[PDB]
Amino acid sequence: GRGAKRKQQDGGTTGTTKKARSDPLFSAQRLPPHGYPLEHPFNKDGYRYILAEPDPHAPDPEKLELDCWAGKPIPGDLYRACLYERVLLALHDRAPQLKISDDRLTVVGEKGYSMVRASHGVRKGAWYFEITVDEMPPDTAARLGWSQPLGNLQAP
Amino acid sequence: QNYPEEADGTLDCISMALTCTFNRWGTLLAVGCNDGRIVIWDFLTRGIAKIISAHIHPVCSLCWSRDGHKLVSASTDNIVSQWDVLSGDCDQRFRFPSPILKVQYHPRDQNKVLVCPMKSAPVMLTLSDSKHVVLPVDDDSDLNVVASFDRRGEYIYTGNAKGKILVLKTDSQDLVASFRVTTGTSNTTAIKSIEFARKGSCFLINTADRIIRVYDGREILTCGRDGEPEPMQKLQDLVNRTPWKKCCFSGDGEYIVAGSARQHALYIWEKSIGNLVKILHGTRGELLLDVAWHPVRPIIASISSGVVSIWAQNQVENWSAFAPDFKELDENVEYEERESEEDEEVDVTSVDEELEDSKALLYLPI
Image 1 (spheres, rainbow over the protein chains, first blue to last red):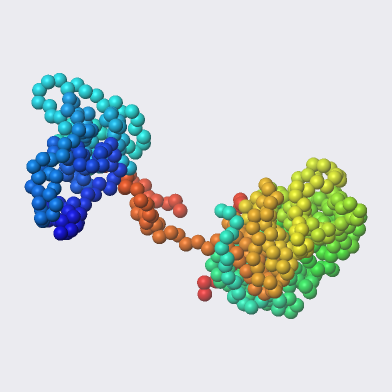
Image 2 (image 1 turned 90 degrees about the vertical axis):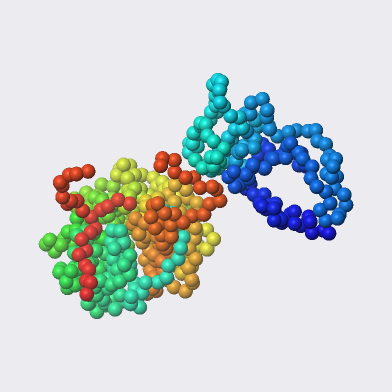
């Protein structure tokens, strides 16, 4: 009856394993260390993992004690890790090697190549915006421009 | 680079080896064997060049000519002969009334050899006409005097056995400068020898007051007839009081090396700071004969008791030298990738400091 936790820890057989790998310097995210609005950019380019907008699930996996998420999930009212009005870049489709401020204004890269994408599309209207390059040390490429989510977040 | 830090073994092509000296940058070794023969070994190539049947009584010193065509030898049986480097026979033969201590060839005058007779004034023997010219000395003429050239050999310096040093010209013999060594605090001191370098005109003096001193070959003709002694550093050994036998100058012009007699303590200092930097760990039991570094590359090689001990810098290039675009190093940082991804008719024809002690012309591949 205690094998369910081991199955959940090893990885199970539900597709991708339950053992995250984001080994570059990942910061500016994953603030609340509990079951709340969270995010995990993954090593594998193209993995977006988020917990905001929660959901219940079916209880009683292996006739253990009744889980609290049976029909009445626990509530949550705290920090949510995203932005609505105009996403300053993003917090979901990113690489786990980018350092951003708490207010999400500055972007600091890794020892190697890195990028940040956004989460807002443009179809009509004026979007005359700016990227103020605070500083650029030698051997630090600073190419900027629009791209697509299909783009590999670590590819040049 | 810096002082030698590795140790090398011995180089004994034949069992006995008395004297050694480098020619200009350590090309060949002049071994005067204790059997009346003159052997030439190869340096930086680990071989032999020529064996000469000089005479019966063994020799005790060796030097080569400015043009490299002669093999002078301060014989123990007063055979002042000019052995040929090429054929090995004797070119010029002469006899001196007193034996010879220090033989040298002026890098600008090979005609006048350097001779240091005992109880008599130094004599320059001219190889062009076999004529002997006595160097004028001062006061006594029966002292243990040693004569030696400067860097360029343009002035000759002589040391006597009462406390007097003389300065004169290598060819004009205009004795116009003298010098009196310090008299300690109560008792005077004689001079054992002096030794020069190839850059800076500095020279060490070894005396009988158990202390090695250093002067420069520019403050005697500047002071005039005779002034007051004023050495830079009165170096000495103040824990064992080892006497000094043979000591030469550096292969760069900034170091000073001094040799023991039986204690296997080879001391080194630098002219800028008179502070000890390293000491040689020699195995006790043998008497040191000759020391002379590589005149360009820092290394030490001391001959003793028929064998030779070398403390050196053994070097083999790193494995990462396969190609400039190929390296075999270790790092834990992410790789920094690249960020920037005629017709003429002319044939090809093009193929310390340097002095004139060259043209040995001695090499037998077979």
